[PDB]
Image (cartoon, rainbow, N blue to C red; front, side, top):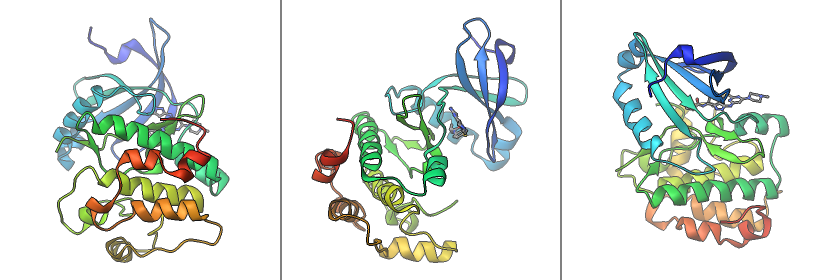
Length: 257
Ligand SMILES: Cc1cc(Nc2cc(N3CCN(C)CC3)nc(Sc3ccc(NC(=O)C4CC4)cc3)n2)[nH]n1
């Protein structure tokens, strides 16, 4: 049962990226509302990411979780590749941060729990994620967080969300994901990521040194969690279990494990 472009009514543009456009779309026969990402073969090849996309699509299709954006299917015609994706109505966590400036501790701990649950599920499937950016986190109709990128591995670019071992030219494993949780926890609470700078060169130095401070309003429990996640040595970061069992998380999160 192969899909073609004619099987979908195309709606308004959802996002405009470097590689292609994402549209709201509705499959004609079922009236199923979904997102359609359109990519040009010529452009993926010229950047040498066609294969990379194929591997990430294949990994994605194996993933089934309420907090991971679902890939339903794919197809392609003469010049274009089409990804058929779950439509998340409430948009990105990035836009929500822009509207709200920063999040309270309850929203933040809920998002972290949801992230850690999705990542726990991924780890048990030997799936590692690369850096997790807010722009790549979507919100479902009940405001549930959805990991929406395709940055998965089975064992550049802005630096803000990358761990030291990835920038220094070192060996990286599942502990990258816990650094990611650290950066996001901080950004949710503060309104910018902990190593933000005006230049790449300086962001590099800040991440490599783990050079960041907290504003005064950050509570002791949040401080404790972020500091444990942001360890330079990957093997010193806690496990996802320990994140989900952290007192600051358990005291503030609206959602369980
Ligand atoms: C793919 C997708 C996108 C959506 N939903 C939305 C919804 C949205 N909104 C824009 C702002 N209004 C106020 C709310 C809805 N804005 C974007 S902007 C956007 C577009 C694409 C991606 N991500 C991807 O395409 C992933 C596959 C790599 C992230 C954000 N995406 N559901 N599914």
